[PDB]
Each structure stands twice: as C-alpha cells, then as structure tokens.
Amino acid sequence: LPIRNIQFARYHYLAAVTVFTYFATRCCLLDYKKYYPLASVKK
Amino acid sequence: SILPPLQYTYSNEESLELLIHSIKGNKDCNSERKAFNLCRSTVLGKHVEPEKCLDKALVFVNCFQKVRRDESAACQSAFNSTLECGKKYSESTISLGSSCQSQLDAYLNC
Amino acid sequence: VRLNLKSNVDQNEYPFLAKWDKDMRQNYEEYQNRIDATTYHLQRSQRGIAVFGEWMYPRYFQKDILELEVLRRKQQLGKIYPEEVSSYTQINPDIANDLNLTFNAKLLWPVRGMTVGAGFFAFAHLFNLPYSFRLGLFVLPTAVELAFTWGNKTSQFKSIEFMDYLLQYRVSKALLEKNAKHFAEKKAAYQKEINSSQSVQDLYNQLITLVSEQAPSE
Amino acid sequence: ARLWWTLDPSKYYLKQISSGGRNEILFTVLGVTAAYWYFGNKRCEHYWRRQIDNCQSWSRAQNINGNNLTVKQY
Amino acid sequence: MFKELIHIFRTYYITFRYLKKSNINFLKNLSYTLIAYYLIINFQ
Amino acid sequence: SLVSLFKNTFLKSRVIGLSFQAQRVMAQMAKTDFENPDEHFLLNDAMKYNELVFYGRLAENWSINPELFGKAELAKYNEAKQTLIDFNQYHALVQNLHEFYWELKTIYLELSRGVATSNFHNKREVTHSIIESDIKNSIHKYIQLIDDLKDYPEWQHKVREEIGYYAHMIYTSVNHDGNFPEIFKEFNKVDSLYYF
Amino acid sequence: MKLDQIISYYITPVRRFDKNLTAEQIYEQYQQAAQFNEIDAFTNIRFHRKFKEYIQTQEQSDYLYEKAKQISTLAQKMFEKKFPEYYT
Amino acid sequence: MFSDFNMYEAKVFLKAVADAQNTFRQTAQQENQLARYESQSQSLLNGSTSGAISITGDNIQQGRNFKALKEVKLFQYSNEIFKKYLAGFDSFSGDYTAFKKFLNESVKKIEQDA
Amino acid sequence: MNHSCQKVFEGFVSALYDTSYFFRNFGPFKATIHYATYANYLAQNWAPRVSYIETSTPAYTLAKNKYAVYIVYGLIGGALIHNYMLDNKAAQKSQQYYLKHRD
Ligand SMILES: CCCCCCCCCCCCCCCCCC(=O)OC[C@H](COP(=O)([O-])OCC(O)COP(=O)([O-])OC[C@@H](COC(=O)CCCCCCCCCCCCCCCCC)OC(=O)CCCCCCCCCCCCCCCCC)OC(=O)CCCCCCCCCCCCCCCCC
Ligand SMILES: CCCCCCCCCCCCCCCCCC(=O)OC[C@H](COP(=O)([O-])OCC(O)COP(=O)([O-])OC[C@@H](COC(=O)CCCCCCCCCCCCCCCCC)OC(=O)CCCCCCCCCCCCCCCCC)OC(=O)CCCCCCCCCCCCCCCCC
Ligand SMILES: CCCCCCCCCCCCCCCCCC(=O)OC[C@H](COP(=O)([O-])OCC(O)COP(=O)([O-])OC[C@@H](COC(=O)CCCCCCCCCCCCCCCCC)OC(=O)CCCCCCCCCCCCCCCCC)OC(=O)CCCCCCCCCCCCCCCCC
Ligand SMILES: CCCCCCCCCCCCCCCCCC(=O)OC[C@H](COP(=O)([O-])OCC(O)COP(=O)([O-])OC[C@@H](COC(=O)CCCCCCCCCCCCCCCCC)OC(=O)CCCCCCCCCCCCCCCCC)OC(=O)CCCCCCCCCCCCCCCCC
Ligand SMILES: CCCCCCCCCCCCCCCCCC(=O)OC[C@H](COP(=O)([O-])OCC(O)COP(=O)([O-])OC[C@@H](COC(=O)CCCCCCCCCCCCCCCCC)OC(=O)CCCCCCCCCCCCCCCCC)OC(=O)CCCCCCCCCCCCCCCCC
Ligand SMILES: CCCCCCCCCCCCCCCCCC(=O)OC[C@H](COP(=O)([O-])OCC[N+](C)(C)C)OC(=O)CCCCCCCCCCCCCCCCC
Ligand SMILES: CCCCCCCCCCCCCCCCCC(=O)OC[C@H](COP(=O)(O)OCCN)OC(=O)CCCCCCCCCCCCCCCCC
C-alpha cells in the first residue's frame, strides 16, 4: 500500500501541469498591442 | 545564440560614465537631438543624401560632448558622487537594495 | 516623427527618387503606429515581475522582436513593386511565395487544399458516402493547407533579407539618378572605348590582380 | 456528477523493477551529462563573440547560378 | 485527465465508439511523448 | 563463447520467468470480453502481458545451445518454450474472435448512427441491400463459429454471450418485414430465443 | 533581463572618443578614415591581409585601418610629387 | 539602479548618438566612393586608350604598352615604400602593442622624409 | 450503391485490406513491428520514476530506494547551480580578455 515519495509525485505532476499550461496558453505573457491606443505617453 | 554580439567593449566604469552623461544630455540638449532625428527620418535625409543632415548632426554631437566634459565644479562633484554610487550598486553581488535615483536627481539639477 | 505626406522631391528630374519618397511618406504613419504598439507591448512586458515578465523578457518575446524589425524595414522601404521582387528572384525563387506569407498584401485561399477536398468529394460521390463525411473531408485538407500556410515565421526572415537587398538597391539607384547628368560625358566617352558591359569595379579588381601578378616590381 | 480530480500517481505506473526501485539515478546521470554538454556548447558560442565591421567582412555577391549579382537600372 | 477526455468523447460521440482501447492507448502514448517533448523544448 | 553465454542466459531467464506467469495472463484474457481482450493490461495492470507477447517470438525463433544447459534445466526450458508457444496460439485465437466481434459491432454502429437522434442529415427509413447482405453473411459466419466450438462449452458460451449480443441488438434495430425472415433465418433457430 | 543589462546592448555600438574632441574633430577623423587614394588599391591588398592576424575587437580594427589610411595618404602625396605628369 | 524612465531616456539618447556617428560615416563614405569610381573609370579609359591593356568581354589582357600603365607605376612605388620605410611588415610576429609601436615609428619615418 | 460502383468499392477495400495485411505480416516488417511495440511498452510503462509502490518491510528495502529522490534532486540542483556559476565565470573571463585586448 505505501507509496514512496507520494508528495513529491503530487508536486511534480502539479508543476508539470502548470508549466505546460503556462507555455501553451502563455497566460502570463499577454499582448498589450491592443492597449496602446488606451495609454498615455511620456517625453 | 540569439542575443546580438557586442561591437565595442566598454569597461564598467566607462559604461556607467557614458550612461549617466547620456541621461544628463537627454535633458540638456533634447532640442538638438530632436532636430537631428527629424532630419534623419526621411528617405532623402537618411539613405540617399545623408550629408544634408551633417550640420545638424555636428551640432548634436557638440552638445553631447559639452555634457560629457563636466565644466562646473558642482557638476563634477555631483557626477562623481553618482558614479561612485553606481559602481557600488553594480559591484554589489549580494542582494541589491537602495537605488541611486537621489544622486541622479541631484546631478540632473546641477 | 510626424512626416508630411507631400514629397519634396522633384518628379521631373528624379522620378524614381520621388516615387519612393511619396510611397514611404504615405505608409509611414500606419507603420509608425504599428511600431509604437509593438514597442509599447515589449516594454510593458519587460516591466513585468518574475515569470510574468523580466525573468523571461528577452528570450521568449521573439515574435514581437521579429515583427518590430519587419515593420521598421518595411516602413523604410514604404512600398514594394513586382519588378524588384522578380529581380530578387535570382537568389530566392520563392520570394513571392514568402513575401505573401509575411505581409497582408492579398488574401490567400488554400487552393491546393480545396482541390484535394474536391477530389475526396468526387471519391465519396463515387462510393456513395454520407454528405457529412464528404463535407468533413473537404474541410480537413483545407484546414491542413491553412495550418501549413499561416504562421511560417521563416518567411519573415526571408522577407527581411529581401527588404535589406531592396533598400540597398534603391539607394544605389537613387545615387545613379542623382549623378546621371554628371556622368553623361564620361559615359559617352567610355562606351566607345570599352565594348564590355561588365561593371567598373569588377574590371578594376581584375586589373589590379593582373598588375599584382604580371607587372614587374622593379 | 462524480468527483475525479486528484494529484495522486496512478497505480498502473507505480511498479518497481525486480532488483529495486526504478532506474532513477542511472537516467539522471545521463540527463545531467547531456545538459552539461548542451549548456557548455551554448555558453561557449554565446560569450566568445564580437562583431567586426570593416571592408574585409564584405565579399562579392552571386546568384544561385554562381554568376556575379548585378541588377540593371531598368 | 486524459482518461476523462477520452471517456467524454466515447460517451457522447457515436462515431468515436469505433476506436478500440488499443487505439486509445496509442493516442495516450503519443500524447504523453508530445507533452514531454513540448516541456523539454520550450526551455531550449 | 562469452556472447553465447550471455544470449543463452538472457533467453533462459526471460523465458522461464514468463512461463510461470502465462497461466495468469491467459486466464485474465479469458476473463474479459472480446471487445478489448487486453483491456485489463492496458488500464489496470500489465501482469507481464507485453513481456509474454514479445518473448513468445523469441522462444519460437531464437536458437538454443544445449551444451550451456543442464539436464533438468534443459527439460524446464523446453517446457517453458512449449508454454510460450501455447500462449502465442491462444493470443492468435483471441485476436481472431475479437476482430470478428468488432466486425459485428461495426455493423451495429452503422445501424445506430442511422437511427441516432442527432442524425438529421442521413436518416434512412428502409435498410439498404448492402448492410442486409453484410448482416446475413456475418450471422452465417457466427453460426459456423458456434458450431466449430462444440467441443469447448465454455468457449462456445463466451462467444455467444459476447458476439451474439450485437447480433441481438441488430435484430432489435429493424422491423420484421421485407427480407427479415430470410436474413435472420439462422439466428431465429436458437440464438434469438437465448436473447429474450 | 533588467534594464541595467539591456542598456548595455545600446551602449556597445557607440564608438569611444575622447571627451575633449569637438564634433568637427570627430568628423575630420571619420573623413581621414574614409579618405581615398589611388595607391590604396595596392597598399590595401598588402595591409588588410595582414590585419586579419590582429583584429579581434572593433577598436583594433579602427586603429589599424586608420593608421593604414594615414600611411596610404602620405604615400599618395609622395607619389604625386614624384610623378607630376600623371596628375596634370 | 535608475528609474525605468531615465533608462529609456538613456536608450533614446544612445540611439541618437549611434545614428549621428553613422551619419558621419555615411557622408564620408559616399563622398570618397564617388571619387573612387571616377578615378577607377578614368584609369581604365586611359589604360585602354594608351594601349596598356585590352578589355574584351569580361577579361583584361596585357597590351604592348603595359610597362607604361599608371597602375603599374603605383604598384612599383607601393613596393618601394613598403621596402624603404615599412620594412618587415609582411612577417612581424609580435604583440599587438609592438605592432602599434612599429606602425607609429614607420609613420614618423615616412613623415620625416616627405 | 450502384452495383458497378459496388464492384469498384469492393475491389478497392479488398486491395486496402490486402496491402495492410501484407505490410504488417511480412517477415522483416513483422519483426520490426514486434520489436518496436515492446520497445514502446518499455519506454511508456517503465520510464524512470521517483515514486513507486513500496511492498517490502523496512528491513528488506535498500537505502538507494530511500534516498534516490534526494540524490536526484542533489544532482539536478547542483548541475543547474554549477552551470550558472560557469556562465558567470565565462562572462567575467570574456569581459576581461576583450578589455585587455583593447579599450
Ligand atoms: C520506435 C519506438 C517507439 C516509438 C513510439 C512513438 C512515441 C515515441 C516513444 C519514444 C520513447 C520515449 C518516450 C518518452 C518517455 C515517455 C514517458 C511517459 O509517457 O511516461 C508517462 C508516465 C506517467 O505516469 P503518471 O502515473 O501519470 O505519473 C507522472 C507524474 O509526473 C509522476 O512523476 P514522478 O513524480 O515520478 O517524477 C518523474 C521524475 C522523472 O525524472 C527523472 O528522474 C529523470 C531525470 C532526467 C533524466 C534525463 C535523461 C536523458 C538522457 C538522454 C541521453 C541522450 C539521448 C540521445 C538519443 C539519440 C538517439 C539514439 O521527475 C523527477 O525526477 C523530478 C526532478 C525535479 C528536479 C527539481 C530540481 C530542484 C532544484 C533545487 C534543489 C534544492 C535547493 C534548495 C534551496 C533552498 C534555499 C533556501 O510518466 C512516469 O510515470 C514517468 C515519469 C515521467 C518521465 C518523462 C520522460 C520524458 C522523456 C522525453 C524524451 C524525449 C526525447 C526526444 C529525442 C529526440 C531525438 C531526435
Ligand atoms: C479557422 C481554422 C480552421 C478551422 C477548421 C479546422 C478543421 C480541422 C479538421 C476537422 C476534422 C473533423 C472531422 C474528424 C473528426 C470526427 C468526425 C466524425 O465523427 O466523423 C463522422 C461524423 C459523421 O457521422 P454520421 O454518421 O454522418 O452522422 C450521424 C451520427 O449519428 C453522428 O454521430 P456523432 O455523434 O459521431 O456525430 C457528431 C459529429 C457532428 O456531426 C453531426 O452529426 C452534425 C454536424 C453538423 C451540425 C450542424 C449544426 C446543427 C444545428 C445545431 C444548432 C446550431 C445553431 C447555430 C445558430 C445559433 C444562433 C444563435 O461530431 C463531429 O463531427 C466530431 C468533431 C466535431 C468538431 C471538429 C470539426 C470542426 C469543424 C468546424 C468547421 C465546419 C465547417 C464550417 C461551418 C460554418 C460555415 C459558415 O462526422 C462527419 O463526418 C462530419 C464532420 C464535421 C463536419 C462539419 C460540420 C459542422 C461542425 C461545426 C462545429 C463547430 C464547433 C465550434 C467551434 C468551431 C471552431 C472552428
Ligand atoms: C542514451 C543514448 C543512446 C540511446 C539508444 C537507444 C536505443 C533503443 C533501441 C531499441 C531497439 C528495440 C529494442 C527492443 C527490446 C530489446 C531489449 C529488451 O527486450 O529489453 C532487455 C532489457 C530487459 O527487459 P525485460 O527483461 O523485458 O524487463 C522488463 C520486464 O518488465 C521485467 O522487468 P523486471 O522487473 O524484471 O526488471 C528488469 C529491468 C532490467 O533493466 C535493466 O537492467 C536496464 C536498466 C537501465 C540500463 C542499465 C545499464 C546502464 C549502462 C549501460 C552501458 C552501455 C554501454 C554501451 C557502449 C556501446 C559502445 C559502442 O527492466 C527495466 O527496468 C526496463 C527499463 C526500461 C527503461 C526505458 C527508458 C525509457 C525512457 C528513455 C528516454 C528518457 C529521456 C528522459 C529525458 C527527460 C528530460 C527532462 O531492457 C532493456 O534493454 C531496456 C531498454 C529500454 C530503452 C529502449 C528504447 C529507448 C528509446 C529512447 C527514445 C528514442 C526516441 C527517438 C525518436 C524515435 C525515432 C528514432
Ligand atoms: C478564431 C479563434 C477561435 C478560438 C476558439 C476555437 C475553438 C477552440 C476549441 C473549442 C473546443 C474545446 C473542447 C475541449 C473539451 C475538453 C473536455 C471537456 O469539455 O470536459 C468534459 C469533462 C467533464 O468531466 P466531469 O466528470 O463531467 O466533471 C464533473 C466533475 O465533478 C469534476 O470533478 P472535480 O470537481 O473533482 O474536478 C475538480 C477540478 C479542479 O479544478 C477546479 O476546480 C478549477 C481549476 C481552475 C483552473 C484555472 C486555471 C487558470 C490559468 C490558466 C488560464 C488560461 C486561460 C485564460 C488566460 C487569461 C486569463 C487568466 O477539475 C477540473 O476542473 C478538471 C479540468 C481542469 C484541470 C486543470 C487544467 C486544465 C488545463 C489543461 C491543459 C490544457 C492545454 C490546452 C492545449 C491546447 C492545444 C490546442 O472534463 C474533462 O474532460 C476533463 C479533462 C479535460 C482535459 C483537456 C486537455 C486539453 C485537450 C486539448 C485537445 C482537445 C481537442 C478537442 C477537439 C478539437 C477539434 C477536433
Ligand atoms: C537514428 C537513431 C537510431 C537509434 C535509436 C532508436 C530509437 C527508437 C527505437 C527503435 C525501435 C525499433 C528498432 C528497429 C527494429 C529492429 C528489428 C530487428 O532487429 O530485426 C531482426 C529480426 C530478426 O530477428 P528475430 O526474428 O527476432 O530472431 C530470430 C532470428 O532467426 C535471429 O535468431 P538468432 O538467435 O540467430 O539471432 C538473435 C539476435 C542475435 O543474437 C545474438 O547474437 C545475441 C544478441 C544479444 C542478446 C542479449 C544479450 C544481453 C546480455 C547482457 C548485456 C548487458 C549490457 C550492459 C548492461 C548490464 C546491466 C543491465 O538477433 C536479433 O534478433 C537482434 C535484435 C536486436 C537486439 C536484441 C537484443 C536486445 C538485448 C540486448 C541489447 C540491449 C541492451 C540490454 C542490456 C540489459 C539486458 C538485461 O527481423 C529482421 O531480421 C528484420 C531486418 C530488417 C529491419 C532492420 C534490422 C536492423 C538490425 C539492427 C541490429 C542491431 C543489433 C544490436 C546493436 C547494439 C549496438 C550497441
Ligand atoms: C465555425 C463553425 C461553428 C458552427 C457552430 C455550431 C454549433 C453546434 C452546437 C451543437 C450543440 C449540441 C447538439 C449537436 C451535437 C450533438 C452530439 C451528440 O453527442 O448528441 C447525440 C445525441 C442524440 O443521439 P441519441 O439521443 O440517439 O443518443 C445516442 C443513443 N444511441 C447510441 C442509442 C443511438 O444528442 C443530440 O444530438 C441532442 C440534440 C439536441 C438538439 C437541440 C436543438 C436546440 C435548438 C435551439 C434553437 C434556438 C433558436 C433561437 C432563435 C431565437 C430567435 C429570436
Ligand atoms: C471530437 C473531438 C475529439 C478530440 C480528442 C482529442 C484527444 C487528445 C488527447 C491528448 C491530449 C491530452 C492533454 C491532457 C492535458 C495535459 C496534461 C499534462 O500536461 O500532463 C500530461 C501527463 C500527466 O497528465 P495526465 O496523465 O492526464 O494525468 C495523470 C494523473 N495522475 O504528463 C505526462 O505523463 C507527461 C510526461 C511528464 C510528466 C511530468 C513529469 C514530472 C515533472 C518534472 C520533470 C523533471 C525533469 C528533469 C528536471 C527539469 C527541471 C530542472
């Protein structure tokens, strides 16, 4: 019954899912070209 | 590698000196820079006949040189303080902390 | 810079140099807006925190940098005419096929995909398949054609190379036109003495080599 | 509906080899060696570079036919 | 997760019933290989 | 002959080790149905199934070097090799039955897609001749198979319960008119009564 | 990558000049670097091939080519004095 | 170190400075390239007319008056100067600083005699 | 369908079935498929792993199987950190070399 390093397995699976989703969706690396008209300017 | 290679190797001291002088220049002589950029934007002024821009370019360069050569004693003192702070910040491999903005503002107001 | 649209070149004396300037100024505003949008996106992304930003700014925002370079070069060129594309066909036979996939010049229909779909439709009609199957088998090759057509960022690199070539060619052509009157007399004298059409630079390099080889040092 | 989400590993892939645990150290050694080689090559290529721009960096262009590239002023 | 997607497609799509458990397993293996390749390559 | 020693040791180890498991794997294969006989091994636990499938060929083909074998060891290896050959034949039989089952299930799936509620585009009132001929020949082959398994009551019962299920569903999918009496003539003898 | 590192990629392409040089002196330096003399067509062949053995950075290229141009200009003046006929 | 605003100010200014230096380079190069083309064209015309060389198709052949060609005189004087003043240049396996010193001394020697 | 098209379709499907069967059951092709199937099974179901079912009493389990995870983490972390340090050292070396060569 005992599973060696089960917690490590859970965290590894979670990390794999997170990384794959991050790269596939690029959720964090959005595009802001659509916001440029709605932005102020300097200089 | 995808990052572009370097052309001129700048010492860290030289790099900081040029960077600070550039920040000062963009305030002191923005007019000359803007005129030069305007004259270098057109096709005729950029590629075909760049010499029509030459005079403007010269003016700009002169201004920048004048900034690079700190003439006032106060300017020299402020620049040296800012440069020393920048060197200390750069050499600090340990977790970085306070910024050098105060010295830069003091220098830009000289 | 907000350059005016009215070119200041004389069309009577420098026609091509005037046309180039006119097209550049005409498209400059639009390409400048696109360039500004791209640069704003780049800097705002670089302002991010950790994975959302800086930690991976330079390396993962590659398509944006490629778009920025393409936009800058195209803005400098302004407009591209088929004569120059056919000229560059020497070194890249697929220049038109690559320059169509980089710029929004004309609408591209997956004609090969649609032809394969029609062939599958004929097959199904012969073998009496349900119409849903043949509509799906028409969509599928079309989808494959579209997938293999769009994207293709290598075509953008080839477009950049072609645009660099075209800019150099246009600059040299402008220099030719500007000094054409000055060289009229020398040209008239030269054509009557040299029966070759090879360039002066090539002939002079060959002459220099000939001197370096055969001429006595003395 | 039935709840099914979970982070636990599946028992189908949890078996060991006869002689002990799965070949983890043996494969990690190979992975580390490959990473060392790859990153060493990348670093060596990246850091030892400079851009030298002078007349000697330019050569005469040519077509895919090998002839010299020249375009008329048509 | 993958199992659940396959289960939904099997239970809702009549055509998908044509696939054996063996073909489903082959798709599973290919998908795992592609996921590993994606994870590895994105960091290169 | 060091390479011969290693080859023979590898063969002995793998073959003898798997021979002790062939009973379990074959029993498990029998336990499941014919739709996916290896379902348990793909989903729950691969009890040395792929190992048996791979090493059966090696047992059949790869040569042996008796001088590297003992007396009792050689007898044991021959016994294990025979067991692996038996497993090969058993797997072939199960595969044949499974593919026939999938033939019948393909026919049923076509009918079901025909009568599906979402099928707003390919709704047919009257069964066409091609599928009728396919049904007739499939049922003929199924009856012949049932006859051929008269010496194996368990196998015959399993074949009925598994394959004839979709024959019964096909029976239920259509009305009792047209050519129905002729198409299901063989099925009406015994099988139809079983599926009531 | 923080701006402190990126700015290095905009500082690298700037040639280093003494801060006490007026713009006109810099432009004169560029003119001398790009000067043209007929004799170059030969001396260059004997110069560039050599410099490939020493150039590793842009500053080395600048210095070596500028010295080559200076030598070639002096040689051109000497040759013009020697052979006035070809230059009348 | 400095706020991002100042960093972008520096970036813009440095871009402008690099463009200015490129402007100097472009001006000088265009002027000297025009001069070079004129000189080379004139030299080829004089060579062909003088009978020094024969230019046919894509090939230059030695004429009967080859010894009088101006380019021949230029080559001979280049050899003369590389011998008298810039001696040892062909094979000088010294340090970079040594090479710079050698070039400077050769320049001084040429200046003195000119 | 039309009985002529029926003949054509039956012939075509028979040809497809025969081609598939021949390609799969040909001697060399059969051997290739048979070996590759087992190789794929080994790769998929016996890939390196850090979590596994422990069915042995603590007295009958090796130390390697209690510290394999820690050894793997040590190896990977050490590799990453050492590569980072090597990158920094190479940066410094290149900077110093090209500085001492000129400017
Ligand atoms: C023709 C043949 C047939 C073809 C068929 C078609 C398809 C192709 C098939 C080809 C065969 C191979 C396919 C790939 C493998 C598929 C595996 C699979 O599906 O398993 C599912 C199966 C799913 O099971 P599950 O129940 O869902 O559980 C999964 C969970 O993730 C549970 O996971 P877990 O918990 O067990 O973890 C797994 C384990 C796995 O990892 C390992 O152990 C492996 C390590 C890497 C080894 C790499 C070796 C590579 C060697 C290459 C050599 C060169 C090859 C060149 C070949 C050339 C050609 C000959 O992870 C770790 O070890 C985690 C390490 C984390 C490190 C963290 C670092 C911390 C640093 C900080 C330290 C502390 C600092 C403190 C500071 C404090 C400050 C205050 O996976 C597993 O169970 C196994 C684990 C996953 C393994 C993935 C391996 C992927 C490999 C891809 C290779 C692609 C190569 C392409 C080459 C192309 C060349 C042209
Ligand atoms: C822009 C980039 C490129 C985009 C395109 C990329 C395409 C990539 C390749 C796609 C390959 C698909 C085919 C292979 C997969 C398996 C197919 C299969 O089972 O084969 C046999 C199966 C036929 O079985 P059957 O025995 O003939 O049917 C009786 C069975 O009982 C039926 O039993 P069953 O349960 O098996 O049948 C369900 C069947 C579905 O088939 C059906 O039974 C019916 C299909 C038609 C339904 C039409 C709507 C019905 C009314 C619903 C209410 C709509 C209201 C709209 C207005 C609202 C106003 C507020 O489900 C599927 O087809 C499964 C896959 C569906 C998704 C993938 C295909 C997406 C195609 C999207 C483009 C379609 C063309 C453009 C349309 C628009 C033009 C302006 O499927 C086919 O042979 C047909 C394939 C689908 C053809 C297109 C039909 C329209 C689908 C629209 C979906 C839109 C989804 C939303 C997102 C769209 C994003 C683009
Ligand atoms: C590295 C660079 C070079 C790579 C070359 C690869 C060449 C592959 C060619 C394959 C040809 C067909 C093979 C057919 C099978 C023949 C052998 C056999 O039956 O097994 C005998 C033997 C024992 O089998 P068995 O008795 O049936 O045991 C299983 C039973 O369940 C009984 O189990 P048990 O409980 O009794 O325990 C027995 C135990 C006994 O096992 C052992 O004793 C083996 C333990 C490991 C090796 C130990 C020795 C280490 C030192 C070797 C030194 C060699 C020096 C060579 C020098 C050459 C000089 C010229 O078995 C195992 O545990 C099996 C281990 C399976 C490992 C599979 C690894 C999958 C992942 C690979 C990629 C990972 C990438 C990670 C990247 C991640 C990045 C984040 O197993 C093996 O030989 C294992 C081979 C596993 C790998 C084969 C496939 C590799 C594919 C790599 C991906 C390439 C993709 C490229 C793209 C695709 C197009 C090209
Ligand atoms: C012109 C532009 C047009 C654009 C649009 C064009 C059309 C696009 C396609 C549209 C069609 C897509 C169809 C997808 C269907 C997926 C299956 C489904 O509907 O689920 C039913 C089924 C329902 O199960 P159930 O048992 O009824 O659930 C009830 C239970 O009580 C539930 O049990 P429980 O309560 O215990 O569960 C707890 C809960 C635990 O979770 C929660 O409670 C909440 C979790 C919140 C997560 C928030 C994430 C936030 C960060 C990411 C955000 C990204 C987007 C936004 C970014 C900006 C804003 C931030 O578990 C879940 O929520 C399970 C699912 C979520 C797991 C988390 C990871 C999901 C992402 C996986 C990777 C995706 C990679 C995509 C790559 C695509 C490549 C093409 O769910 C599943 O099947 C589960 C597994 C699904 C795996 C999908 C993996 C990706 C598949 C990619 C290929 C798909 C091809 C499709 C055909 C294409 C055409 C031929
Ligand atoms: C581009 C990248 C490429 C590389 C990466 C690829 C990645 C993707 C995966 C690719 C997977 C598919 C591969 C292609 C399919 C190949 C099919 C095939 O072989 O067809 C034969 C097969 C005929 O054989 P058969 O019908 O199975 O056998 C009956 C015959 O009458 C013959 O009867 P026989 O008794 O006269 O001869 C039997 C034997 C020849 O017999 C011998 O002479 C002895 C051979 C060795 C036996 C095993 C001794 C193991 C001793 C321990 C070693 C320990 C090493 C260190 C580790 C220790 C700790 C674990 O010949 C074979 O059948 C050779 C088959 C391949 C090797 C099988 C051995 C596997 C285990 C040993 C290697 C792996 C390491 C395991 C380590 C761990 C072990 C616990 O069909 C054909 O003839 C087809 C020909 C046309 C297709 C292409 C043929 C290619 C041939 C390649 C030969 C490679 C030899 C090994 C090279 C090793 C270099 C280091
Ligand atoms: C780019 C293309 C985009 C196109 C977009 C198209 C969107 C399609 C959305 C489809 C939704 C789902 C239904 C179709 C697919 C069903 C698949 C499936 O598995 O179902 C099988 C099952 C049917 O099969 P079954 O029930 O026989 O189940 C199978 C059983 N055996 C195996 C025994 C045969 O479900 C259905 O198909 C249900 C269909 C329901 C239809 C409901 C229609 C509602 C219409 C509303 C109109 C509103 C108009 C408002 C106007 C207002 C004006 C003011
Ligand atoms: C009608 C329309 C019909 C449409 C049908 C379409 C069908 C498509 C089916 C295929 C696509 C399915 C996609 C599923 C979502 C992706 C999930 C994902 O990324 O993980 C995949 C898999 C684990 O997920 P899963 O197997 O689903 O769940 C297991 C639960 N225990 O992960 C794997 O097994 C991949 C292997 C790696 C797993 C992670 C390993 C540990 C992570 C750390 C590795 C460390 C490596 C070394 C160190 C690196 C860092 C220093």
Image: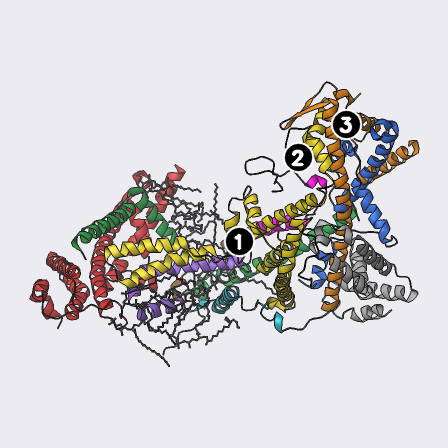
Give the crowd class for mark 1: few <14, some 14-19, many >=20 residues within 10 Å.
some
Instruction: Decide: is H49 above or below H27.
Output: above
Q: What is the chain identity of the residue bearing mark 2?
A: C
* In the image, residue G52 lies in the stretch drawn in magenta: no
Q: Is residue H28 left or right of residue F93?
A: right
Query: Alpha-carbon distance for marks 1 and 2?
Result: 57 Å
Residue range corresponding to the magenta coloring: D37-61
Q: Is residue B96 left or right of residue F82?
A: right
Q: Are marks 3 and 1 in contact (CB under 8 Å)?
A: no
Residue lying farthest to the front in this orientation: C12
Which one is nearer the viewer's eye here, C167 or B52?
B52
| Kind of residue at disc 1 | Gly
The dot on residue A3 is: none
In percent of the image, x 31 and y 39: which residue is there?
A: F65
Q: Are marks 1 and 2 on the same chain?
A: no
Which of the chains is orange? H
Which one is nearer the viewer's eye here, C70 or F32?
C70
Which one is nearer the viewer's eye here, E40 or D58?
D58
Question: What color was chain E assigned in the picture?
Answer: purple
| Kind of residue at disc 3 | Glu
Which of the chains is brown? D
Residue receiving disc 2: C199
Quadrant in the rendering for residue F168 = bottom left
Does dot 1 land on a helix, a strand or a loop? helix
Residue receiving disc 3: H71
Question: What color was chain A assigned in the picture?
Answer: cyan
Query: Alpha-carbon distance for marks 3 and 1?
Result: 64 Å
Residue receiving disc 1: D31
Question: What color was chain I assigned in the picture?
Answer: green
Q: Residue F94 in the image: x percent, y percent?
A: 22, 57
